[PDB]
Image 1 (tube, each protein chain N blue to C red):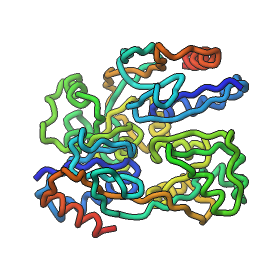
Image 2: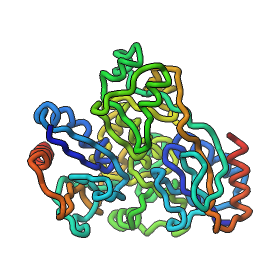
Image 3: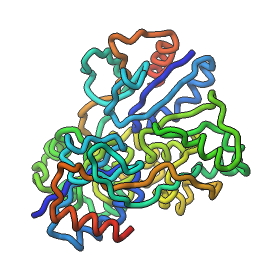
Length: 196
Length: 197
């Protein structure tokens, strides 16, 4: 039984991979082919059964099932965190963002500050995993889904300076419309939505 | 005042470029550098990039590619799996982590004089060596990746290189579309970078 799943790398690392030994013992008859992507994925061209991705749940020709929330907050190194006492202090440093719209402007507005200047030093990332590597090394303040990075928080490599969160999308497991479903697919789906 | 947009494959960004970035900013305060990362599949024309830093053989369609540095690849794994690996064949006690590119474990095993891995061997595919190496730190399997790009993980002992044997399946290049003008800010950057490397 062959199940091929493309997984946004953040989710693979922060959520799924720790859980795959559970899906091993509980369904030892399914041969899981896992590939990662940077949330830009052509499931048809890649021959994926399922796709795990980040966003709002509205993809053309695609049936999406919600998996879990992806609430974002500033994350930074302990070195930078020690110089950050209020949200405006974040603007002492470069901002790290994704290719998606509005992340820093929405977060700043949400906690009652003005958006950053349009010419603030920013670096754009295709993957939150790379973003948080940059942040660990002090390249700037990241904004990403806190729940995918608890291994850095608990190990103290990253700090979350503020409680406020924003919600610019969630994690979805999705299937192309024209894509036949299967029993291994249902069993994974069921198992994963289950644990979350 | 002079603007420069560069897209960088993530591995290179983390393992090489970003640690040097402060030096470029100091030295060339008059250049406004806009950095983005990619996972080595990138459309420079669509993203409006001046330069693309990427991994490969140096020959992309209608592209001028300058050599940056070598990217010799060797198995990398957590300290825990390393403790169970004394010979290359021990690697196959564990799942293999690979990229979308062809033949990395086939070539490396050939090179150390071992048989190819089973075609049914447990393998996970990664779009990024950064993501690959996160997975290896967590013991998902054994990575193979450009060793010189993970000096931070090696020296901090989060990752181990059990064997010195290393293979060339491409290098890092800084590339420019032939149709893209080269500006003064571009010349200064690629000269600064090829220099520091």
